[PDB]
Length: 155
Length: 155
Image (tube, rainbow over all chains, first blue to last red; front, side, top):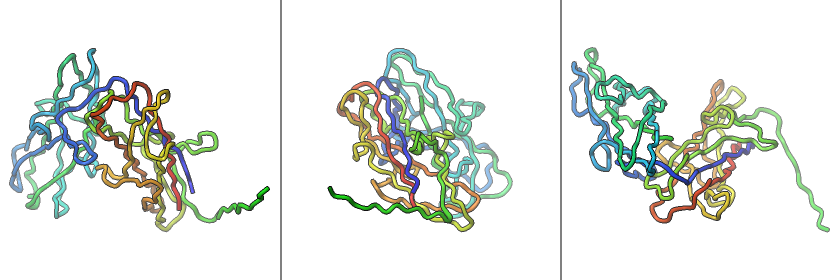
């Protein structure tokens, strides 16, 4: 019998809120990274942007304050922690990655707070740009591949 | 004068130990559930994970032996027994809950042994995922809200 304590805390004072999300039960549904349909072996880098579940556009984070606030954005490694989509039935995997800039260069490194700014009376967008490498080796099995990345807007 | 007996017992043989805790005086400090800063009325479900007081990551329970032991985890209802954080100065309360899975579905029911597995030469993590409902009604007073959940790793 090892009984222990867990201090719970919350500082209600002046915070920042994330728009574009829908409450899926008790977990915020931020959006979808829909690469679309594809064949077994694709030569072009498959690329799609996150579509917020609430509006359809990009996640719009706004801060409830007057002065500028510097908030951070961190995305985790997905269900299996290595950013791989898994086929619903078979065990095939599809490696992918999420970048922050339009040219697939600034990668949202696993469990890292990619910095962000937010200004007076405005909603800043959180671009989560997906990208998949060209698979020109083995044709992955037919079906639907999925993953649930947990995006962590933290301060 | 009602004098009575209390039998004390301890079976020293082959037990299981919880890592990630720090001994706060004579009580094991397991960790912190830090939801962060927030405004009076938040529309998004505030959500944070427990951070072990010893390492900063998740509580890592390991057992001492060779056969996989099945240990249980039970969390209580907090200081007031209804999972509410209380403002340090005023009497305002903030209802919350702790779940076991990443999607806020498998709730750690009050005083219930949520089952767990553990194999030899490995440490299993105890995910205590916090979650707070969207308060879009009354703005709670400014300040710090706290609670001390007692996590009970028992066999």
